Image 1 (spheres, rainbow, N blue to C red):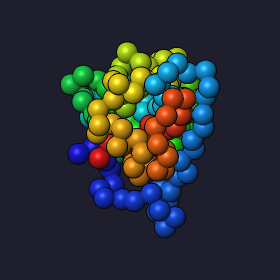
Image 2 (image 1 turned 90 degrees about the horizontal axis):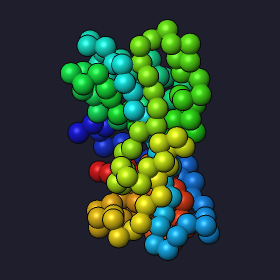
Image 3 (image 1 turned 90 degrees about the vertical axis):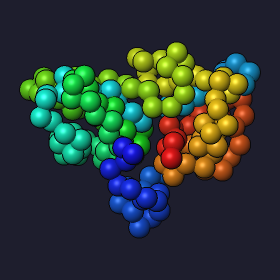
Image 4 (image 1 turned 180 degrees about the horizontal axis):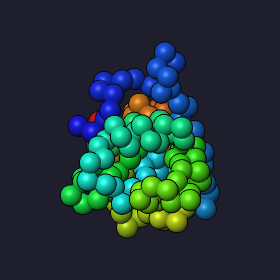
Length: 162
């Protein structure tokens, strides 16, 4: 498992507490939902940079929740606790290029072909989500719908997937 803080809960006593914003977009086609990524793809990762090193360097911009790192592939998938935090990294982290890290929107939920990589969201037809995906979307600790059912046009932040 790739979560940095095992078994944590999205509760007010956790410093990682974040709200779960949900909205509705009438323009989506039938049976489609919109999911904002909380996952960054980081390329240019040096050989001796580990998961906590990435969390440590990012901390002034965002609190890292999970990291899937592969040094042999020079990359990591880094999930942060909120969409706002992910945007803050892309806006403000390493913009001069003092570090070799190269950061962009990643995909942590749903099919890769549904992702708009420029804007960091996916428009996903619900027939392409597993029952597990649908359950995660409604019941996850961070992101998801906070109990609200999945309907055409619902918009939410990337849900945790176990």
